Image (cartoon, rainbow, N blue to C red):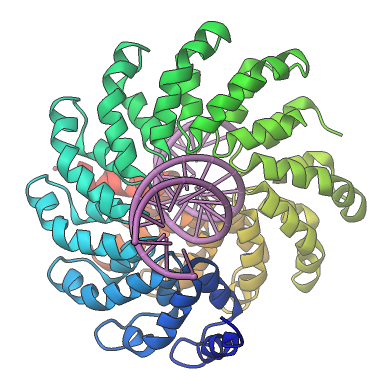
Length: 476
DNA sequence: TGTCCCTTCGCGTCTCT
DNA sequence: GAGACGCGAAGGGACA
């Protein structure tokens, strides 16, 4: 091709126009993963996708387009969404979720073909079939659940929920076959329980982790002194294979030359990217603190960010290492640190918050999301809904802050004016892990019915959604 | 150069209490 | 607070 690059840039240009009104980020996303033909398909069928009986939002179109075969997915969605919705009960969101993976077309056609038999003959729910279908290779996983769910239940004593958990990852077919093949030897030869085998298999690359566990468990227990419980824990994240091999190679070095305990090495290895974290730790602080930063998903990123920003954050923004470590010791530590850097001065000034408050927000999983959302929503929360900034901060200061805030904004009016809860109590329910589910559950029970309104709040604060659901099950 | 499938890394949120 | 859940991005291999 040559200087019909112009034609393609003109096509991308017209997608910025209406019905989709895409921005640069979205165009970039489609180009990077769906390729030019996905970009051309979106342009070609932008009207069909957006109206008719599909009625897709541009965000939904982007999600389908942004994978290998995206053009096939968009074509097939136009063909199958209505029948999947009307005849099989699924919602459009679910159809989009199936379609938003590489090979989306195949998954959608297989769900059409297999959902009935899987529900009727195998007893799955539509929800489970969607979860199986909603990954790359979903066709294969669905077909393998159909062929193997009986043997895995009858001969290997697994539950359908377990089989679904193994199936609901990319390479689900591979993990299910490997479980079928290796479950007996892993239990009988290495002393594992089915549950443990399941936990190792229930992640992406589970096949690889099971074969690695079969291959290295002996060495790691017999020659390096780890327990089977420890080996399993390492193996129970995606990438387990990698973490297991790196443990074998680095355990002697990290204990001999650097003085870490075996239990510290394991804890670092037992996260997604464990291999990465181990290598990075081998390459201000106490070793306890380095381990603590390393011991999360993305631990490598956190450590390299800490090494880069600890000096400036301490010197130019006045923080202590103890605070930097606390920001870094969560999932996405790197993201929180970077954000705190570009958001301490801004939040304190445009919105009048103290540093100590900013640290409390960023010292949780999802810090970047919490801060960025406090920046957006603090003004409307106080001025419109009448909240104190200290209240907004109590809600932001937990894992899932952005969720709890965005939900509070949505649900604060209907909780107070329509059901007589005080804002004092809604803040109390939002100020925990799982604030958003807790609020939703609360509104659902109240909108569409002995547990008076105050008992429901005491329950929602204490145990969130779990407490609320448990209460239903238990009901007399 | 697109389409399908599989694996790994990382980020974000919720459950268990 | 630790351990569990979900999901997107990105890269690799096979085949056309």
